[PDB]
Amino acid sequence: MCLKLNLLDHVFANPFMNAAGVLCSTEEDLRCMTASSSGALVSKSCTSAPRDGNPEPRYMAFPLGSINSMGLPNLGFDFYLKYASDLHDYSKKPLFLSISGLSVEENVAMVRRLAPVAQEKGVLLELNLSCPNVPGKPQVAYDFEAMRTYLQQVSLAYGLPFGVKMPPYFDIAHFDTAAAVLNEFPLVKFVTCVNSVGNGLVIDAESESVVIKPKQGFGGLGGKYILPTALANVNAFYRRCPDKLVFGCGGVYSGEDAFLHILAGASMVQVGTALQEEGPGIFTRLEDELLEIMARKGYRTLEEFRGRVKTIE
Amino acid sequence: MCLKLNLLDHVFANPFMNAAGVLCSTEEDLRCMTASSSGALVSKSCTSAPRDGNPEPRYMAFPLGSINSMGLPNLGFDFYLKYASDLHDYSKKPLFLSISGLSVEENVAMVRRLAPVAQEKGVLLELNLSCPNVPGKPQVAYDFEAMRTYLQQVSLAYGLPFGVKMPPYFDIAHFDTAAAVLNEFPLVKFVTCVNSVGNGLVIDAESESVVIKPKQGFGGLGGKYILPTALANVNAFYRRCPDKLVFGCGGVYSGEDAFLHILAGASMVQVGTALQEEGPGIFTRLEDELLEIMARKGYRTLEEFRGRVKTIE
Ligand SMILES: Cc1cc2nc3c(=O)[nH]c(=O)nc-3n(C[C@H](O)[C@H](O)[C@H](O)COP(=O)(O)O)c2cc1C
Ligand SMILES: Cc1cc2nc3c(=O)[nH]c(=O)nc-3n(C[C@H](O)[C@H](O)[C@H](O)COP(=O)(O)O)c2cc1C
Ligand SMILES: CC(C)(C)c1ccc(CCc2c(C(=O)O)[nH]c(=O)[nH]c2=O)cc1
Ligand SMILES: CC(C)(C)c1ccc(CCc2c(C(=O)O)[nH]c(=O)[nH]c2=O)cc1
Image (cartoon, rainbow over all chains, first blue to last red; front, side):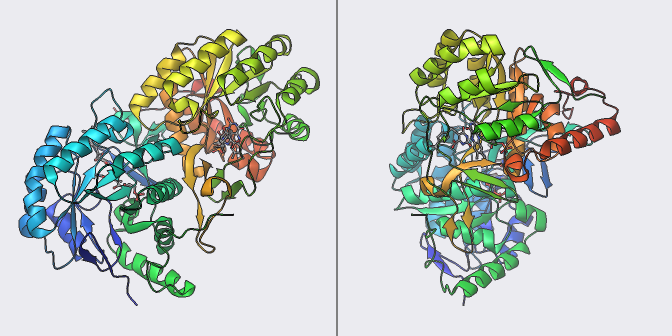
């Protein structure tokens, strides 16, 4: 028995990959992710030009999870484009490239350049919809009119299947609206739920201080704190987007957590905080643990249980 | 060395109270909370008419917290008004009464009738701004024009100092807008942050089932999942509303969690999931734990550290 699957016209040895931003910023990182047992990898969300990111400390983790306000540090789009075009070994696993330009125009200009490499090599685009609206306005995914516009422009500019990275929502009306917006775009073939839970605040009791330096300690939450939120978003989008795939992201530390993501509707399962903390070894463990739960339940394929979470009455 | 506080023209032996909805639905519950060592109590959020609420199971708890979709079960306004005017012993501790009408008009009629009792007995109003909107719209506090509408009419109909129970926000632009709206209303003297983290989904791996019956298993999250979110919201409002009190609510299981809330700016500190799980004995433990932390740091009163969370640079 094996966890192999096919989607977006690619083949994957297993449904696991890193979450964008974790172990994927540098050529060394991407080489490390490629040499891992993961079924795929995704590059750090990039901008046109290189960015240093925010002052450190900017990431911290704890037994229940992590907090970060990295500030989109990245080597720049030319670098990830070149990794996709000349360096990545597509015989090893598929690659996704994440983009998070600081305006619609910057994103349009990056996707136009990405298109021919996508055609030629099969790199897949994950558009990060936590990219900024503007200061003064919520991130783009929490402003449905700007979201519709980004997607209009990117679909026109890119013209090939892509996916989107979504922030979590917390209100059923917002699931209905967000998903209807996404379903206006036939080229949006996968929806990744979720990005970090925005602007939480970790305080250290001993020092009476926040733990990261940017934004007066406020930053996005990952890890155990966000698993039920992540499952709710995957399932809400899975229900509402029957002609798309959903990729689950959030609070994956075990094969069990991955199993619940898939029950919720996930096709692929991304690993952030737990990967940052444990390292790329985690993928062999996660595969073994998911195959073990499967064997005990008698499931031979992921298809047999994906999206089959039971409701009560 | 003192946990005492004086606010809103009342005296409180300590900053702890139940979170609305926990251990506060029936006369028996409210007498139990009064007999406890809590510094105050709040009644279950009520509607004009009694309600049975949603079908069961509708609440479940786990090591890292709870999920609920209770559906506002409650004995009706007349019962909580009678408890406030005739049954509560104000010599023991102060009472808050929470209301959560299903329309602006329902809220207006309850506050008109609460007003004379508030004036005469000193019962304090907590207006629940997660009260449900017209369905297919977001909850009232995620719809800034509905929120403004509710607070104008309640200010007018009530005419006395009150507070508001807020859902969590996840986006800085949302903090800024919400606090600006609250700051339009001088009678809003306290802001309770936060209500449950909306529409999470808990899935049981063994049974492959959601754990609550309503809303296909979607419900609000409390407990350890939500502490950083709750701390972020406390501090965001503490900083943006210098003329109002902030009450903290979310993820309190220990004197240490309470300490972090208070550092973030909390005055009162409410306890939901951990109280539902542990019972009212929690309050003695919480007081002893918080006093132990204070003794170790040389703090003699709450005001010596309230809101004094340090940032880095
Ligand atoms: C250090 C760090 C960097 C991140 N960078 C990105 C990014 O560049 N783009 C992105 O879409 N999400 C990014 N995230 C969010 C993750 O991809 C993921 O959605 C989130 O951490 C929740 O998953 P987890 O619970 O497994 O951590 C980052 C997370 C962390 C912790
Ligand atoms: C069973 C249950 C019932 C609740 N009912 C109410 C309510 O009637 N009104 C309200 O404002 N909040 C209600 N809440 C929210 C709690 O007041 C609190 O805001 C939330 O549970 C987070 O605090 P915690 O993490 O200590 O649980 C309820 C929570 C639970 C778990
Ligand atoms: C330019 C600035 C407004 C500082 C900014 C733009 C875009 C992002 C998104 C990158 C990202 C980050 C990050 O790099 O801080 N962290 C996450 O948890 N998720 C993310 O999606 C983060 C920060
Ligand atoms: C279950 C649904 C019909 C969506 C609903 C009705 C009413 C309320 C407000 C009461 C409330 C409840 C509740 O009674 O379900 N639970 C919370 O965690 N916080 C609350 O504020 C919250 C939720």
